[PDB]
Length: 28
Length: 28
Image 1 (tube, rainbow over the protein chains, first blue to last red):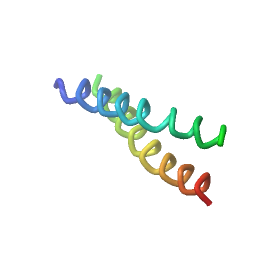
Image 2 (tube, rainbow over the protein chains, first blue to last red; image 1 turned 135 degrees about the vertical axis):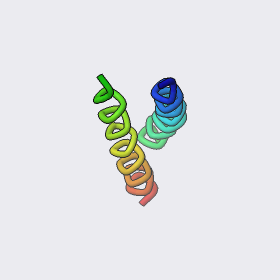
Image 3 (cartoon, chains in turn cyan, blue; image 1 turned 90 degrees about the vertical axis):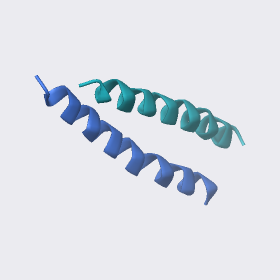
């Protein structure tokens, strides 16, 4: 029942890791 | 009631497919 929160947190972590790297690569 | 979990899993799969491809394209 609470696995939805776990997968949402995993999505949040993955997005917060990926997005700034993409922004920095675009700046470069 | 549980369709929220299904659509969240679909979002997770779509993001996990798309993001590394974008990173590789930026590297190229």
